Image (cartoon, rainbow, N blue to C red; front, side):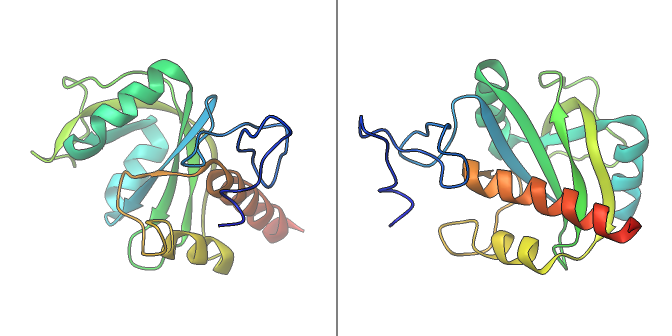
Length: 167
């Protein structure tokens, strides 16, 4: 609990990576919010990367729409079996039950439009570690919200991994 007690002078929790970012007491930023998508279907991700659409499950739809209305929301995409990084995107529309992708099913409340920031298919060991511990030390649940510092690390690690493969 050295993260949870990392504070400014006023006792507000702050990010460990960016001290300018104030967090609530679950380590979440008011302005940039991050959700993990565990991808088990190569055809779905190929479709999502081409058409900039994703499906939101019923178990996480309410939290995701709450966040979309209050902050910038990002989805970080990771292969289910390996935690390979697949990319990250900003959510740029609210849930639309009419615009679901072909691969969705009754577990999904609706679709959202996204704007891709990075796309790749790469293993990053540090990405895998973060995802392995995202649910209070246990492995991530699909669609869960992560802490600001987790999202910021994942995005940088994806950016760095892509950058390094070009070289």
